[PDB]
Image: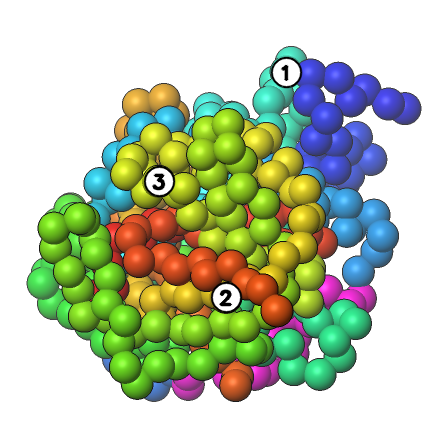
Amino acid sequence: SDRVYIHPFHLVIHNESTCEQLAKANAGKPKDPTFIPAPIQAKTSPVDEKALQDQLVLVAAKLDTEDKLRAAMVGMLANFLGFRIYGMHSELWGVVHGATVLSPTAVFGTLASLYLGALDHTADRLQAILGVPWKDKNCTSRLDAHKVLSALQAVQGLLVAQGRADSQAQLLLSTVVGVFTAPGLHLKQPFVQGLALYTPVVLPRSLDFTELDVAAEKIDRFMQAVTGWKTGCSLMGASVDSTLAFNTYVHFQGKMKGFSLLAEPQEFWVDNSTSVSVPMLSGMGTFQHWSDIQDNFSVTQVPFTESACLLLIQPHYASDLDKVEGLTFQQNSLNWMKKLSPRTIHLTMPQLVLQGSYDLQDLLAQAELPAILHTELNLQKLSNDRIRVGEVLNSIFFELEADEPEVLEVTLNRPFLFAVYDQSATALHFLGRVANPL
């Protein structure tokens, strides 16, 4: 049958036949096997990043044509959630931790993973927050987490692809989900298998939250040891009386062929008066670029196998970004910006190597007000014992690199906007602003 009214997102929701299996397991007779995670003092081996991406490309390879549409679908949901989140109205950067850049796909995922640990009401709220509407309070109408999570795994493999390239594409996307519970918090098994679908690197490990100072310093010492990249602090703004700490950690590598790091700095102006000593990346090549004269716009790119594309949004005047940048989180327009007009361009931009943390509960509020919904009792499917979340953090480590008759000298001397986007998963993995490198 076909009942895809209300919303067109028919792939991410539950099916009756899939719910018939859930109906069998719905009985109370099978009790789930909980487990306490070990302390972080335990010697945990670091993440083999090669081994990770080689597994993600396999996931992308061994993937149905139906799954590709699902990956595209969950991509758009992540897009719309990111544009929804701009309902803060230029307060997104107000969450001032590290460089101003957020990951719509990571946000969606971290939010979708909390959905696993959610009963009625709480799951029924996150359902909406994620973006998929519902009706009737039925099983058929409810969002499927296991599908959404493994679909969102796919979108990562779709980004780091190099299908026609074959050789090392040079772009990397690591995503390690820390789930730090309190001492004696027996977190459930099937939830953790759900997280496994979203990312292979799922690291649940216990911690003493009564001492926030001691927890925060050790939580950084653990992750930076396990991951191998400096994250912009951790456990910031977490309460003393807390237990759970669901922190997603992402790392983006983005090598651009036909580029080189300069020993001599060109310097930049964060504003007309002030100047900053900063590195650069010169670029020679015929890319696609077209400037909208209606709202005064201009955007160039430096594709990663077309599939993935780094779009650099340049404000034509560069006087008022907040107004122009608003049109870079504007619903269907940012995606439909796709004239594909090629031109000879001399690309010139600062060398980007910055961290960035942001708590989802601070990132989302009022319109969705999850901060309240998070400290609400209803979780269960994750929480055996009492859960009171201190922070649900998304930390990114965005990194750009180089591999050695007429033109357009496109320099980014003043602040600009950017966003990496995947065509194959119709999903923008990152969006951010650059005031100054520091």
Q: Amino acid at mark 2?
A: His
Residue 317 — which label? 3
Give the quarter of the image for residue 45.
Answer: bottom left
**Residue 176's spot in the image, x, y percent?**
45, 66
Front tag of 3 and 1: 3
Quadrant containing the N terminus in the rendered view: top right
**Residue 247's spot in the image, x, y percent?**
36, 56
Q: Is residue 360 left or right of residue 139?
A: left
Q: Is residue 28 left or right of residue 364?
A: right
Residue situated in front as seen by the camera: 48 or 273: 273
Magenta span of residues: 45-62
Say what secondary structure mark 1 lies in: loop
Residue ID at (67%, 55%) = 342
Residue 437, above or below 117: below
Residue 259, above or below 214: below
Whichever of callouts 3 and 2 sits on the residue coming sooner in the sequence is 3
Say what secondary structure mark 2 lies in: strand
Quadrant containing the C terminus in the rendered view: bottom left
**Residue 58's spot in the image, x, y percent?**
73, 72
Q: Amino acid at mark 1?
A: Lys
Residue ID at (59%, 30%) = 332
Secondary structure that dominates the magenta span = helix
Q: Is residue 141 left or right of residue 262?
A: right
Say what secondary structure mark 3 lies in: loop
Residue ID at (64%, 13%) = 136
Residue 135 — which label? 1
Specify few, some or many for label 1: CA neighbours under 10 Å numbering under 14, 14-19, or 20 or more. few
Q: Is residue 285 left or right of residue 434?
A: right
Residue 20 shows in the view = no
For residue 53: magenta? yes
Which residue, given by chain and number where applicable, does mark 2 sit on?
A: 346
